[PDB]
Length: 259
Length: 261
Ligand SMILES: NS(=O)(=O)c1cccc(C(=O)CSc2ncccn2)c1
Ligand SMILES: NS(=O)(=O)c1cccc(C(=O)CSc2ncccn2)c1
Ligand SMILES: [Zn+2]
Ligand SMILES: [Zn+2]
Image 1 (cartoon, rainbow over the protein chains, first blue to last red):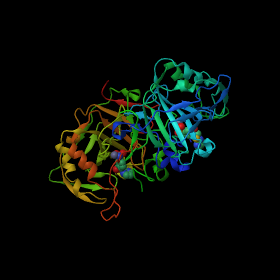
Image 2: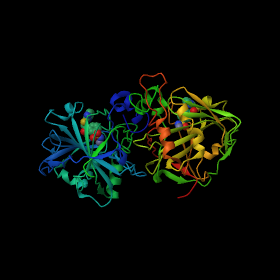
Image 3: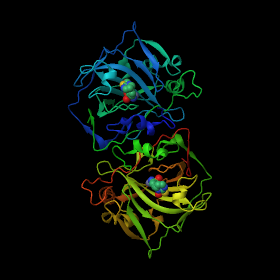
Image 4: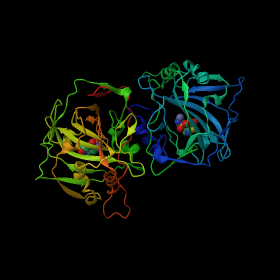
């Protein structure tokens, strides 16, 4: 599967039936579908300050760049405890640097970070959790152009060692909480899916209301570093526009922690 | 069959209609990064749009939209070939989210969208043979927003409660179709794309007018609530709502504009 051409997103449903099933993400966050829920409590991020003496595997999986995260990282504030598994990014392209997955009032942001967690009270690991009830919880951070961000540079500075699919490098531990915005207590919450194949309708989404900033140069670096193909592919393809279009969202509601 | 909701909705069109997964797909979001002014883009001329009030035209609930048949003497001039009218129809949302245009502008969905469909009659016999052939189709798009009552749109809308179910027809006396067009029709977006409905043929030259028209809250609600996708006999009716396609990726391409910004 890809994001462009014949095996692009309108064809995902052929090999991956859930990509044309229920609860699909991402969506456009707009007033007609929002409802304040005063019961939603702020999340607490535990174990996110990773030891500088430990290291963490960065991988180009052919679709994005992922960081592996340890199952001792947890979020509190959902009904079950959810432990971390990986984080990754979605982005656009230099001529159109508007590649977030979720939109707000129809507007794309430059990019989007996802911090993926699985239900560790119910399930032993992420792979088992991925296609089961209540299995996954993703945190989403919207990214715009702004000031240089030292914390996102903790990922971006390694990008030239993972240029082709399958390549790996280690990244020393850093504080994952520095990737999060201001006032995390304000967010949108809804039931949805993976935004790539296999598109399992098994995800609890929390999209923070406030965006972070990365510089133009950091954004351009991310847009131009990577390839979807293996180092010996005779038809190389750049890793750009790796985001899904927003999905229909009807007779259903997104809940907000802010009124 | 195909729908806009459930197992047969738009993510699964590609399974029965392989062009829906192919190149050049519409609709799109019209936004600054992909727009460029083209000064060679001249006004279209609308000929035979003033339909005979002594003639009647067939309006049809086809299970996916409400469609008005148009005569072959109606046409657009100004493109390389003459394109002759075949039909017009609409796309809308629903009363809880009344934002069902197909094209969007700077991420803005309008309330609804009118399409006036033409075929290249210099090169081909009729619309169905023009359909899957190169530069076979041209479509005019009007973006609709909620506001003032519109007498000309009501020439169509006043029939809606008499075509509520699939297969039903009414007769509409001729009126001036140019009166469905917005102000300053010389200002438009232009690009190569596809039919927005299966079989999604990548054969459409698009013209989307810059300026929206308005219809009243009452007219928009009648459009959103009058009609069903299913036959009159159906024990389980399905409402004809949300009959618009999501915007499509549009990468390394350009939409040209006849107005400058
Ligand atoms: N963009 S996303 O966070 O919804 C996303 C898409 C696909 C996989 C993931 C994961 O974190 C791994 S869960 C998984 N991976 C492969 C196959 C099945 N599930 C996240
Ligand atoms: N929404 S649209 O203007 O792009 C559109 C949708 C569906 C059909 C049509 C036509 O009538 C073109 S002729 C045709 N109709 C159905 C199938 C194939 N060709 C136009
Ligand atoms: Zn993701
Ligand atoms: Zn149409």
